[PDB]
Image: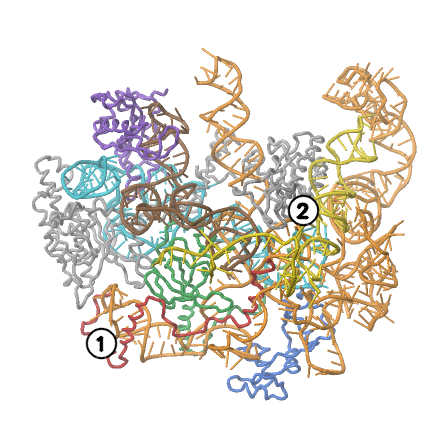
Chain colours: A green, C purple, D blue, E red, G cyan, H orange, I brown, J yellow
RNA sequence: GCCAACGACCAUACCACGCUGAAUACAUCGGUUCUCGUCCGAUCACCGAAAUUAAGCAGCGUCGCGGGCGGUUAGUACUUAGAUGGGGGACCGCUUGGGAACACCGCGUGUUGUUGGCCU
RNA sequence: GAUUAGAGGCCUUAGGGUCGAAACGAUCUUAACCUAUUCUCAAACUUUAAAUGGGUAAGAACCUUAACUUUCUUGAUAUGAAGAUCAAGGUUAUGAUAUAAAUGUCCCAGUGGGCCACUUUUGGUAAGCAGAACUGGCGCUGUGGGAUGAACCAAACGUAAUGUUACGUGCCCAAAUUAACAACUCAUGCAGAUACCAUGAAAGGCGUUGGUUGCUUAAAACAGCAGGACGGUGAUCAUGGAAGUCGAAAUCCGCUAAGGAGUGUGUAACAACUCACCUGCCGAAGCAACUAGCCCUUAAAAUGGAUGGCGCUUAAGUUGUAU
RNA sequence: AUCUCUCAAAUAAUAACGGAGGUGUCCCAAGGCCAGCUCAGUGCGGACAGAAACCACACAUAGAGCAAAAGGGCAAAUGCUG
RNA sequence: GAGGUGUCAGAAAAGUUACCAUAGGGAUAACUGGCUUGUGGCGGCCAAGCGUUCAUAGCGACGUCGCUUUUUGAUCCUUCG
């Protein structure tokens, strides 16, 4: 009859997944985050002074706090419906980077350079993003082994 | 209180445990899960046969015991006592969910209209997927007419539709019969009680070498 | 395994490094009573070795002998270096040092137990009491502190780690203690 | 895909589609065709289209002005295809109607429009 | 009286009738609940940016007054 | 026993196996305040061997740890110190070495002259005004115990007397009697000038010839009597204050692929054929008997 | 090709066993006057080297364990979506698209930072 | 965690012993144990692990660059961080749209009891019961269609004419008893008839009609009618008989195309005696279990009446389908 | 009112008099923090020495401890000792 | 800050009326119908055996799976003007 309160429902979430227990790495005690370096909020089991509570874990956010050994985030969570902002304070080793910006920054500097090579011939930019297309119309020699090549099933009886 | 047999044709209650937390569990009397000459080697019984069903059918605990006794009496009256290896491959860990209705005699007079509805254990049952092999016999090849024509009287204790497989394995092992021969011939199948040894090559040397020694000398 | 030996002439696997020295001797006074039995045992050890005796607050109450936790039940001590080699040979005459077979552990160290602790050249002094004692001397190889140093601390392997024969060699070569496989 | 029946048209469908049951959408209203004017008046400078067979050209041949070349159309009002719909039950490839039909859309649009 | 309660039914459908709407959108967001100062240290530097044409170039000759900065390349 | 015991096992990392760090000190050593972003914390490293004591200056980064400054007792042969490379006297000049070597790097050779005439002076240097903020320094004790009288503080002592900047307290010095100071400040004048060792030569000068054949050996091999030790230090210290040579070395080179040398690792063709060299022998040992 | 210090990623880096290790070294080893802890100068501590390459450590070997990683298992199992699709229900067959895994086979057995120094 | 089977063992935990005074010599066995496995399992067990759905991001509120700013705890570039201000800058950076987007009051009248189907699902044996998460709908809603029925499936309702479709055509019923058939199915007291839906299971059929796998036949098989069928040996097991025969340890053969220590009517002896078998006879298909469409048994209600009525039967019927 | 493990369909949220339980305390050390030093077991051991004590040595991935229920973390610690 | 509100956002609070008088309720029973059937009447199946012999004349254990609504509870769907 309960959630209500403060750490219930942490079966596979809040601990350490397999073969990573014990002493923390020291890479994540080194990282640096400016204002606007978009970052994630996730779970941990090796700094037991601080957590993001039962709903947040698995969400990412902006950073507008720079402090002693903490990070204060903006994050969106579902109320019904007034989806608000929330300011959560947390010690740093709960937190991983976004890599979702980390494709986009090399989407920038290619476009500053591929326009820069375009600045000698003019046409054309072609600088937006497009997924795969309907391709072509080949003609295909066998070339490699003419047809039939006939796999027809018969397998049930066992 | 040994409720009638129709009430558990469907696995629709939860996959239950048997805990070290709840005391009060009665006895599942199935203390035998295999009959026949269990002291036989693999070479004694080349033939294999199972008995299998075709549903997600829940199977009661009781006809397992009938499945023990009924095919036993045919096989001890037909083809010798020790010429087979009966195996009923299935453990009834699942529990059924009962409130007992011994609310009589007047001195108690409240318990339950349906407030509340907890459970108590009285027996067990078994949960069967599709093609789950249940009742199997490992015998010699000369008693195929003995086992299946005794297996009729065990199929009519396990409910619903059931098909009958004749294996192509060499007994209860995990090896096909024609596959069984050629890898046995040198060292690669080392004999044991009900099974064999898969690939003694790894390792690293001496176990291959000790198996190399006794087949030469 | 599949590793060529070929014996480069820097050692015949000789003895500059397996020179087999005594790590320590442990003296234990297992008395089944605290208090007066403790302090009468306590004035013994201060002239056997001259060391400050370390006692033993007991584990728990097994109830079988009326003995409990924290009892200070017994006396013990450790002695190593320049003092252990003389108190052992004062015991070997009491031990009649042709000792029995076991008496021995496979670690390369061993020990024994005695009655009548007066005969190592001490005054009896009947105010102190008679006492049966057990002993345990620890041999070793110099370099064994790698399992017990604070830094860069590693284990041994099969060598230079000892077997029961190494002490049984050292028991029979020097002090001439024949093994008594009895 | 259970609720839409999408297909790839021929020549004669798309010529006949904007012609027969085509309307156009200038100033977010729906005033149909009646001349060449209803494209040219509002597709002349910033886009390069001014005849009805040129609006063909930026759809049937597919090009880089296409995305503005069919928000320009109001959705049509196809009638109902006589002979019927054969079942309307399932996807195409068991029973037959909606889905990945992609080539037999032309036998529909000869009727439905 | 056990009738039917506790239940989240239809309640979502009535929330997606007015759109779900990330709070507003803003540019110069508020600054509250932080380190309280840091914040007023900017207030000094907010009083500091006086030159776009007058003092911005006077220091550049004074950069060369110490013949450049060859020494402190690590600190 | 212990078959599947390997499967659920995992380790403590690499330097815990070889016993190099602790991960408990260093993390809360290099726990940089995150408000400062990547201004380095710049700790000082001192490690020791049975023959040598070492002095490093390093700081952490994201990939690892750049070590800007280094020292050994191996350089002290250039400064008149022949033997006794594990002395508290020897601990002083080593910390004194890098204490101006960084001052050549940043050019702060003039300012922060440090404690000049050392006779055991508790001199925390003052932060100067109107110019260069002084380069702070933090102390690591590594894995050794920071008891009152450890030699690692002697490496700090030449560092703090050379002009380096440490939040530094005095209760862990050798000679400062813990019950109770009473700061006998002249005890480091006996420490830094090696008199605590130089008495042991003099108090064994007439007792045992075999004492010199024992420890403080090789002083007799160079005629080092128990009188002149402090002036070897004092002449080294001004020479340390003259210039550290910054370890110029130009052999360049006899290093590459000598000789092979470390048993290149026997690929798949020479693995199974070595097995094939071993498989055919065992059937031959059976074919010998028949 | 190494060695040290500091590391970093923290098993391809581990463990069992066997073998080697030039130099630099690391160590091992030795003493107890002072710092100094100690029941115990063994662990700690101060002094420094006679002896040592045995161990440790490094390097390597093992159809070694372990782990990394590939290929098949397998479009199988489960599955979002759809139906005037059957069946007595149980449960399964199709349309729609994502799509596994242990086992089973093979390959691999530390990569590297800066700081020095060594030179087989 | 719980859990089934034995095996492999130097075992010395060793329980019974055993050859031995015990054995300490020796020898099995049985309990332990380890080693390799093996049958199964998990709502409160996890070494990996999906689809569906969570989260941010997909630039001019930019992106690089200068030196300025800092009354600072940090840091000597009096770095760094953020700030203001110049310098360079493509066409703004995924698709598809916008029936228009954007907000402050009245806290504005109501309403704070609900119901259901599919999957997913607890409680209970369970129900047109309760208890829910994610949708769609019913209340608010008519409607064309299963006669009927708030939800089923088509479609969501300004007044009108025409044309045309998601269920169904013998007829009441508007439309075929089709210039569309292939087979299907015989029902003796409800044969069956259009999903929910208002039913029918466990087990058979020399009922039929399709099959798979086994055999065997033209050196003529089956069915069908001809000859033989015991002795060596009452050697033998069995005496309530064994002599061929309730039941047989055994055990061959002789005889011969074919006769076996024998097939025989709850034959107690010998016997009588026909089988098996071979050949005559006839000469193209036969036979064993197996699998699964419909009918078929199953299967029993009280007012007399229900595919919805009339009714149908190389259909108006159960199935795949043409137009 | 209030706490956990599930019940919960891998974001969170959530049901019934559903299941297993828990709490109205306790601690100047069971707190604060530096220091040293690693337990569960199990092997071979050792007068009196088994289930008996105590010392020694190896294997000890945590099979313990951490006031209390149950989860979670926990290995020169968040435990033992000081 | 504490003394205090454990029915935990906070009234200070014991009974029963077969003499009981009212607003009403099917949001809530006893009775009548209604789907369900653990209960019980009710048959099927395979045969472990019994039946002197003989499994199946009649029987049919151990277990296997099925209909009715007489009761027995279930549930609260309708009638409390």
**Dot 1: chain letter:** E
Image coordinates for residue D112, horizontal then vertical, percent: 69, 76
Residue A154 shows in this picture: no
Image coordinates for residue G116, horizontal then vertical, percent: 23, 54
Q: Residues within 10 Å of mark 2 (few under 14, many from 20)?
A: few
Q: In this view of the protein, which residue sits in the foreground, E15 or H129?
A: H129
In this rendering, is residue H166 above or below G5?
A: below
In this rendering, is residue G41 above or below B98?
A: above
**Dot 2: chain letter:** B
Identify the element where label 2 is drawn. Answer: helix
Q: Which mark is residue F100?
A: none
Identify the element where label 1 is drawn. Answer: helix
- Rounded to the nearest angstrom, the CA distance separating label 1 from label 2 is 95 Å
Q: Nearer the viewer, mark 1 or mark 2?
A: 2
Q: Which residue is mark 2?
A: B7
Residue at the spot x=60%, y=37% of the render?
A: B27
Residue at the spot x=18%, y=64% of the render?
A: F107
Residue F10 shows in this picture: yes
In this rendering, is residue B158 above or below F63?
A: above
The answer to whether F59 appears left or right of H61 in the picture is: left
Q: Which residue is mark 1?
A: E59
Image coordinates for residue H315, horizontal then vertical, percent: 85, 62
The answer to whether F252 appears left or right of F278 in the picture is: left
Residues under numbered marks 1 and 2 in contact, where contact means CB atoms less than 8 Å apart: no
Q: In this view of the protein, which residue sits in the foreground, H56 or E4?
A: E4
* Quarter of the image where one finds residue C138: top left
Image coordinates for residue G68, horizontal then vertical, percent: 44, 51
Q: In this view of the protein, which residue sits in the foreground, B147 or C121?
A: C121
Residue at the spot x=51%, y=70% of the render?
A: E20
């Amino acid at each position: 009859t309960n959630s209500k309160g403060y750490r219930r429902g942490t079966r596979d979430m809040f601990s350490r997944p397999f073969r990573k227990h014990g002493v923390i790495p020291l890479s994540t005690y080194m990282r640096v985050f400016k204002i606007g370096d978009i970052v994630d909020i996730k779970g941990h089991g090796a700094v037991q002074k601080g957590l993001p509570y039962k709903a947040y874990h698995g969400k990412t956010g902006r950073i507008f706090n720079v402090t002693q050994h903490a990070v204060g985030v903006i994050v969106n969570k579902r109320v019904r419906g007034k989806i608000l902002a929330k300011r959560v304070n947390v010690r740093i080793e709960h937190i991983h980077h976004s890599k979702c910006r980390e494709d986009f920054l090399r989407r920038v500097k290619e476009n500053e350079r591929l326009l820069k090579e375009a600045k000698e011939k003019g046409q054309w930019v072609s600088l937006k993003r497009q997924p795969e297309q309907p391709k072509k119309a080949h003609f295909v020699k066998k070339l490699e082994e003419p047809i039939a090549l006939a796999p027809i099933p018969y397998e049930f009886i066992a | 209180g040994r409720r009638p047999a129709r009430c558990y044709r469907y696995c629709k209650n939860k996959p239950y445990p048997k805990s070290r937390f709840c005391r009060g569990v009665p006895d599942p009397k199935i203390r035998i899960f295999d009959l026949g000459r269990k002291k036989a080697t693999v070479e004694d019984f080349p033939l294999c046969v199972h008995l299998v069903s075709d549903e997600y059918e829940q199977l009661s605990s009781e006809a397992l015991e009938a499945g023990r006794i009924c095919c036993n009496k045919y096989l001890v009256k037909y083809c010798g006592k020790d010429q087979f290896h009966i195996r009923m491959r299935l453990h009834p860990f699942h529990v059924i969910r009962i409130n007992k209705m011994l609310s009589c005699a007047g001195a108690d007079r409240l318990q339950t209209g349906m407030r509340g509805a907890f459970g108590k254990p009285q027996g067990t049952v078994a949960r069967v997927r599709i093609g789950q092999p249940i009742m199997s016999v490992r015998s010699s090849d000369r008693y195929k007419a003995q086992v299946i024509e005794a297996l009729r009287r065990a199929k009519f204790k396990f409910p619903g539709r059931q098909k009958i497989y004749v294996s192509k394995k060499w007994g209860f092992t995990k090896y096909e019969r024609e596959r069984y021969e050629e890898l046995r011939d040198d060292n690669r199948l080392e004999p044991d009680g009900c099974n064999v040894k898969y690939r003694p090559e790894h390792g690293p040397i001496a176990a291959w070498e000790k198996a190399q020694r006794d087949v030469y000398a | 395994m599949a590793a060529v030996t070929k014996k480069i002439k820097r050692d015949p696997a000789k003895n500059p490094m397996r020179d087999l020295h005594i790590r320590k001797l442990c003296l234990n006074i297992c008395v089944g009573e605290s208090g007066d039995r403790l302090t009468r045992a306590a004035k013994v050890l201060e002239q056997l070795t001259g060391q400050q005796p370390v006692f033993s607050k007991a584990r728990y109450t097994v109830r079988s002998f009326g003995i409990r936790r924290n009892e200070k039940i017994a006396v013990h001590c450790t002695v190593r270096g320049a003092k252990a080699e003389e108190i052992l040979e004062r015991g070997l005459k009491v031990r009649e040092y042709e000792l029995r077979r076991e008496n021995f552990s496979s670690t390369g160290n061993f020990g024994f137990g005695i009655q009548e602790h007066i005969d190592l050249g001490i005054k009896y002094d009947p105010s102190i009491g008679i006492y049966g004692l057990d002993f345990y001397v620890v041999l070793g190889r110099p370099g064994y502190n790698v399992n017990h140093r604070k830094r860069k601390s590693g284990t041994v392997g099969f060598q230079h780690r000892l077997t029961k024969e190494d002490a049984m060699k050292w028991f029979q070569q020097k002090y001439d203690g024949i093994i008594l496989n009895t | 895909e259970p609720y839409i029946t999408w297909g790839y048209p021929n020549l004669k469908s798309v010529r006949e589609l904007i012609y027969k049951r085509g309307f156009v959408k200038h100033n977010r209203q729906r005033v149909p065709i009646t001349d060449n004017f209803v494209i040219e008046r509002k597709l002349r400078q910033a886009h390069q289209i001014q005849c009805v067979e040129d609006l063909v050209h930026e759809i049937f041949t597919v090009g880089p002005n296409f995305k503005y070349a069919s928000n320009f159309l109001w959705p049509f009002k196809l009638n109902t295809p006589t002979g019927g719909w054969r079942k309307k039950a399932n996807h195409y490839v068991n029973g037959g109607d909606f889905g990945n039909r992609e080539d037999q859309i032309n036998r529909l649009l000869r009727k439905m429009v | 009286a056990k009738s039917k309660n506790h239940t989240n039914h239809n309640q979502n459908k009535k929330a997606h009738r007015n759109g779900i709407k990330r709070p507003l959108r803003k540019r110069h967001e508020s600054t509250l609940g932080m380190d309280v100062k840091f914040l007023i240290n900017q207030r000094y530097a907010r009083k500091g940016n006086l030159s776009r044409e007058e003092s911005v170039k006077r220091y550049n000759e004074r950069i060369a007054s110490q013949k450049g900065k060859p020494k402190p390349v690590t600190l | 026993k212990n078959k599947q015991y390997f499967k659920r096992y995992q380790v403590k990392f690499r330097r815990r196996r070889e016993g190099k760090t602790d991960y408990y000190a260093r993390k809360r050593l290099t726990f940089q305040d995150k408000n400062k972003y990547n201004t380095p914390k710049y700790r000082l490293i001192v490690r020791l061997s049975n023959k040598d004591i070492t002095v490093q200056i390093a700081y952490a980064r994201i990939e690892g740890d750049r070590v800007v400054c280094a020292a050994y007792s191996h350089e002290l042969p250039k400064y008149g110190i022949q033997v006794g490379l594990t002395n508290y006297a020897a601990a002083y000049c080593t910390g004194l070495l890098v204490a101006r070597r960084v001052l050549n790097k940043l050019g702060l050779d003039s300012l922060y002259a440090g404690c000049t005439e050392v006779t055991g002076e508790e001199f925390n240097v003052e932060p100067v005004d109107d110019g260069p903020g002084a380069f702070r320094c933090f102390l690591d004790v590594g894995l050794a115990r920071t008891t009152t009288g450890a030699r690692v503080f002697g490496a700090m002592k030449g560092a703090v007397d050379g002009g380096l900047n440490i939040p530094h307290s005095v209760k862990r010095f050798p000679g400062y009697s813990a019950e109770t100071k009473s700061f006998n400040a002249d005890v480091h004048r006996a420490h830094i000038f090696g008199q605590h060792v130089a008495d042991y030569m003099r108090s064994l000068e007439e007792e045992d010839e075999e004492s010199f054949k024992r420890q403080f050996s090789r002083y007799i091999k160079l005629g080092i009597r128990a009188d002149d030790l402090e002036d070897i230090y004092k002449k080294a210290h001004q020479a340390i204050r003259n210039d550290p040579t910054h370890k110029v070395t130009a052999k360049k080179s006899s290093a590459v692929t000598k000789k092979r040398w470390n048993a290149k690792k026997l690929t798949n063709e020479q693995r199974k054929t070595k097995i094939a060299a071993h498989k055919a022998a065992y059937v031959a040992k059976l074919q010998s008997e028949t």
